[PDB]
Image (tube, rainbow over all chains, first blue to last red; front, side, top):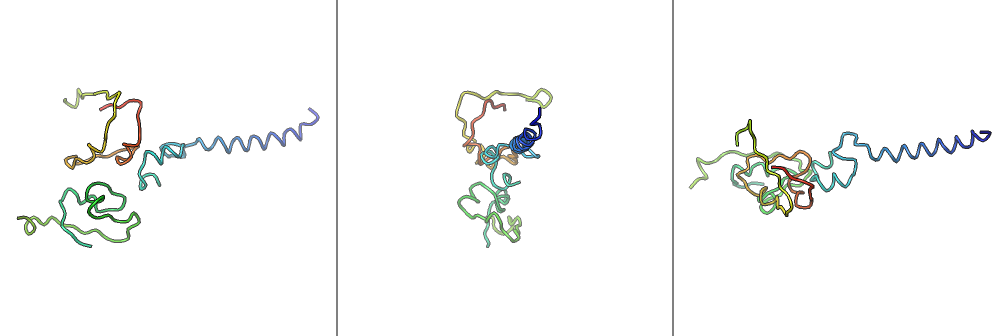
Length: 49
Length: 47
Length: 50
């Protein structure tokens, strides 16, 4: 518990990277967040939207 | 560009389309800048 | 069938060639809502219902 500052600096960066990775799974309104679903299911004029 | 085509196929004369006219007859580029003008011509083209 | 008692067929355990459907100009509409009809022949599905 003395080294709470340094271990928090490690934790903040780990939480930031893990948040950034987990956001790859978010749809943001797309039909899927797996980019290969979109590219395999949709033809270019729909896929680009 | 100009031609006579069957009325049900006119939907294929656009960017991104598919079917026999768009695949083998005449294909627009997918970034086409232009106007597509068509009319039913059965009073003159039919024979 | 009638529209109040609409018919469902489960379609399963097969190849299906959707180009054979999409090529039929009799289909006055063929609107698809999460797949494009050109792409269907490169997919495979866990079930299909007609």
